Amino acid sequence: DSCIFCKIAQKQIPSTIVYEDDEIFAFKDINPIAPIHILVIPKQHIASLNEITEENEAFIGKVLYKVSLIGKKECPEGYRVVNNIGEDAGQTVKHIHFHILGGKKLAWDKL
Amino acid sequence: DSCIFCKIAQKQIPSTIVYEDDEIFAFKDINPIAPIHILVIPKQHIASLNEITEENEAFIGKVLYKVSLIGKKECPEGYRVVNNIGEDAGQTVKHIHFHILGGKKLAWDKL
Ligand SMILES: Nc1ncnc2c1ncn2[C@@H]1O[C@H](COP(=O)(O)O)[C@@H](O)[C@H]1O
Ligand SMILES: Nc1ncnc2c1ncn2[C@@H]1O[C@H](COP(=O)(O)O)[C@@H](O)[C@H]1O
Ligand SMILES: [Zn+2]
Ligand SMILES: [Zn+2]
Figure (cartoon, rainbow over the protein chains, first blue to last red):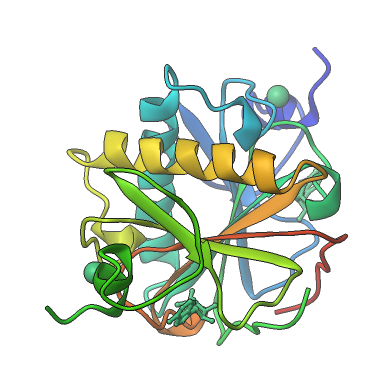
């Protein structure tokens, strides 16, 4: 009812869809920082990486596996995966999302 | 015998250790790009995220869980987790390593 990414996952708010299945939903970042910039979310609401538990760690491993399958397909020359937790990382939406970044030789600059 | 991170994990090459257990090894990046910059590796040799399989996905979930435990302790104000796969991402060592970055409001710049 409230979470922007939960709603995107249920196609209640529009997105450019890259992949979806019963468990995950991947779509293009609307403000990209690389030529390929994809967000991968679980459909289920998990607020951040700090909400991973010993009991859901297998599920998050499966999400990361599916992140790799998307990345190796969309970015055969290589890709970077980023996850932001909390204020210093600039986490905006409190629904866990993996960034897949690629399509160029990606910078590695001081943060 | 050959992999720099396998050797660091077995303390055959020195590092500044942040945490270790029977499964993982975490140490300070020697060329940091943030005030807190930690590398977390499995002790077992896995070359990159592209080597995750349906059969080891639970293990990688556990590694990511332990990444979150390290991050929330070392970076209570928030942290970014990064993984680089292949040439465009600039992956140097072919032994999977998660970057934990924090200690400041981290930039989000074009790559
Ligand atoms: N409605 C949206 N559709 C697609 N991407 C979005 C939308 N709203 C925010 N984003 C992206 O979501 C990301 C949030 O990343 P983070 O800083 O890790 O919370 C940013 O890269 C935003 O550009
Ligand atoms: N001997 C070392 N000890 C600690 N960190 C290292 C060492 N060699 C390389 N690194 C770091 O490992 C990281 C490799 O990251 P990547 O570009 O993702 O392959 C870089 O941030 C390097 O500064
Ligand atoms: Zn949500
Ligand atoms: Zn190794």
